[PDB]
Image (cartoon, rainbow, N blue to C red; front, side, top):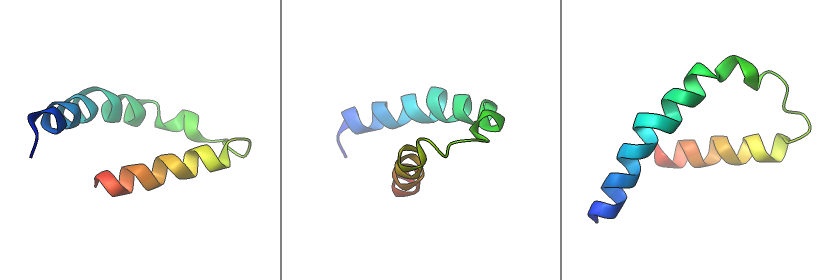
Length: 48
């Protein structure tokens, strides 16, 4: 309920997620940071 959380969500969904959607094809090979990309997916699904 904090407006800090609201502003953070606004920033993420305005800048970061569109940026990662436009740079999605570069996500082809991540076998060397598989743990990192798994953490990304887990955090994104938690936000969802």
